[PDB]
Image 1: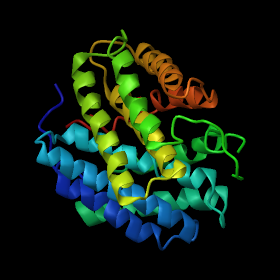
Image 2: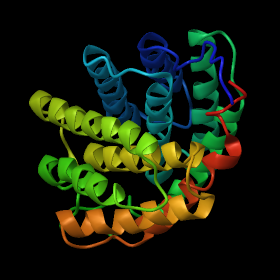
Image 3: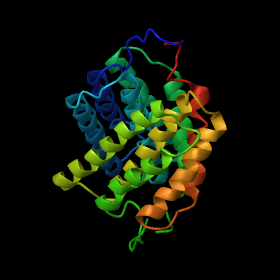
Image 4: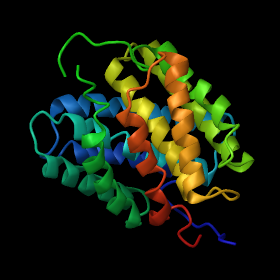
Length: 137
Length: 137
C-alpha cells in the first residue's frame, strides 16, 4: 500500500496557502495575462487560502484534502484564462500558467513535482472548448 | 461575453452554494463512489460554500467568480475520484459524477448548460493517469 507520505506543496495548510500566493506573484509577471484577469483570479486565490485555514480551524486538514484544494485552485485558474484573456493568445496564456505554477513549487519546497505542470497545460487547452464560460451571453 | 445574461446555477450565491449541496446528496447514492471519497468531498462541499459566503460578506461576489467556484468544485470532485475510488471502476465513477452533475443543475436553476457535463467526463478520466496523488507516497 502506497504510504510514507513525505513533504509536498499540500502536506500542510502553510505550504498549501503558500502555493496560490506565490503563484499569483509570478503570474502577475506573465505576458499572457492581463490586469483584468489578475484582479479576478486573485479573488479565488484568497478564497482558497481562507477555505484551507477554515478547515484547519475545524481540524479537518489532511494531505489529500489539501491536495484537492491544490488542483481545485489550479483548475479554477485555467478556465478564467482559457475563456477570456483579453490581451493574449491561446498558447501564451497556457504557457503563462504553467510557468507560474512551476515557480510556486520552488517557493514552497524548492522543487517541482513535475506531473502537476504537465496536466495544467491540458486544462487550459480544454476549458477553451468547454463553452460554459461563454454560454452565448 | 456581452450583457444580458440568463438564469444560471451561479447567477447568485444562493444557487451557487446549493449546487454542491444538492450534488453531494445525489452522489452519495452513486455506485461508483465510496464512503472514503464521500467524506473527503463533503468536506470540500462545505469549503466551497464557506468560500462563497466569505466573498459575499466581502462584497466581492460576482457571476464570474461564482462560475469559477462552480468549476473549482467540479474539478476537485473529478480529482478526488480520478485519484482512486478504491471500490469502483475508472469509468463507473466518471459516469457517477456526470449523472450527478446534470442532477445538480436541475436542482438549482432547473436547466443544464450541456457542454459542462461533457467536459467533466474528461476531468475525471485525466487526473487518473497523471497520478499526482499516489506518487509512490
